[PDB]
Amino acid sequence: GAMGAPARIEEEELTLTILRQTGGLGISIAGGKGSTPYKGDDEGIFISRVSEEGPAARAGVRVGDKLLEVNGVALQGAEHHEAVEALRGAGTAVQMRVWRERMVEPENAVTITPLR
């Protein structure tokens, strides 16, 4: 596999741990695609379900956080089912990684500005 690597910006590396929900119900992700990788192995998974400051989302995610690997399982190219299958048993302790690129991460976010 090798088509190109146009969007390959310096990675930041953000490891987060999501333990069993302590009030809510964890989070909610959804990917699925199966298209050529950005830099050989990358798809970018999105989610939407912030927790009430507990071990479910706030632990690292934030309603739509850029993630690549889920619970140690590279979601690069994988499908929504591949990302959930990892959270199944990891429900008690999930380990997802967050990387920054020229896609998953929107320009609006790339800007480090306040909200006042």
Image: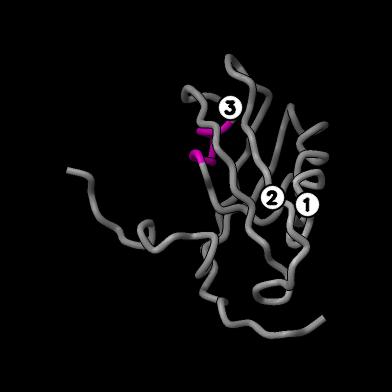
Residue type at mark 2: give it: Gly
Which mark is first along the chain, 2 or 1? 2
Q: Is residue 91 left or right of residue 111?
A: right
- Dominant secondary structure of the residues highlighted in magenta in the image: loop
- Rendered-image quadrant of the C terminus: top left
For disc 1, the marked residue is 79
Instruction: Kindly indicate whether the residue at mark 2 contacts the one at mark 3 (C-beta within 8 angstroms).
Output: no
Element at label 1: loop
Q: Label 3 crowding class (10 Å Cα cut-off): few <14, some 14-19, many 20+?
A: many
Q: Could you tell me how far apart the alpha carbons at marks 3 and 1 are, in whole angstroms?
A: 24 Å
Which numbered disc covers residue 31?
2
Q: Label 1 crowding class (10 Å Cα cut-off): few <14, some 14-19, many 20+?
A: some
For disc 3, the marked residue is 55
Q: Could you tell me how far apart the alpha carbons at marks 1 and 2 are, in whole angstroms?
A: 6 Å
Query: Can residue 58 be found in the magenta stretch?
Result: yes
- Image colouring: one colour
Measured from the top left, where is residue 30 in percent x and y?
Answer: 67, 44
Q: Could you tell me how far apart the alpha carbons at marks 3 and 2 are, in whole angstroms?
A: 22 Å
Instruction: Kindly indicate whether the residue at mark 2 contacts the one at mark 1 (C-beta within 8 angstroms).
Output: yes
Element at label 2: loop
Q: Which residue lies furthest to the top in this view?
A: 23
Residue type at mark 3: give it: Pro
Kindly identify the residue that appears in the image at 51 percent across and 31 percent down: 50
Kindly identify the residue that appears in the image at 74 percent across and 73 percent down: 36
Query: In the depicted view, which residue is nearer to us: 34 or 70?
Result: 34
